[PDB]
Image (cartoon, rainbow, N blue to C red):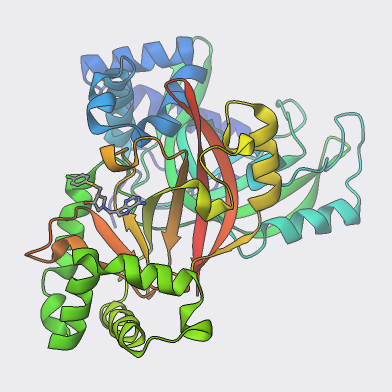
Length: 416
Ligand SMILES: Nc1ncnc2c(CN3C[C@H](CSc4ccc(Cl)cc4)[C@@H](O)C3)c[nH]c12
């Protein structure tokens, strides 16, 4: 056991005084560890906060060069670095109010003036969040204690999140107040909800935990090293026939295979040669299953979501189109008859420059898949191939501006 510089429990619970006392001592202690550029980034954060956090949520979806050249990138890196100066030595339970719309719950739990949360609403919220992972991203201020009477309580939903060991946490002073900054960047699972009473009103307290995953975001180099560490020896694990079919697929055979699968060819017009290729590629993907929870990115064309390039509903620059898209797909399963190519990185690429839908997939540990880019003779980069017939549960949809074009981030989970 590491003896921490300033002792604390994992959860301060309702003890505001003890949490605030510890938070102030920590803010002072970490300030002493911060570089000049990091302290300066923290000063800029106190004066912007909203724009700096918004930037941190979608910065990784642009081209690698657009990221570097962005005017907010240096401040993002300095503030990110400041938070990583305090990776916690043991878990910490945190608290924050959240909008139920964050979990795609679009009904009202209760109004600000209503005191009660009906069992009807409570159970409807439970059904929306149960058995789902939700990606949380960007800079966020959180509390170290359960809010009470004399605390701001802006929504009927209170998150009680266990932050694991080594999560960066930045306690900092802001004039006469103290707060804690985190950068998020994980999947959460809401294990349990309970109706609690704070000052004569019902609130839903959501017991959430971080479900760890690898998510390289724009760091394609780190993603590539991971893929190569786990799949450099993959082609040698295959039979010569499995490898020849994987290579044939990668070398442009994907068109005949994926069109055959999409058109339901194995049922309406069976092709034994193509069926054998599908069987071998599928078996190859089951040889070395994804070893850990892994987040991948796919730049999707409109056809994957029943649209075309000229469809008016594909104009996400109109709010009614984002609303119609979210209503149709959030909480739904998306099935792919074809093999699905994805990247370990979220960056935009010339090949997919204009695609407006970013499918952000969490692959559970043990799923079929392979890092195809670890193959020697293959040119294709950062590629994880997923098995044909994969179904993806869409948890949440978000929008972002890519210049003048609104694009969507579809947060989905590969379902077994
Ligand atoms: N719809 C899709 N979305 C995202 N990624 C993929 C991929 C995976 N790779 C992206 C990549 C696009 S072109 C390219 C080449 C070199 C470099 Cl250094 C960066 C980009 C291909 O090599 C395969 C296939 N289909 C995808």
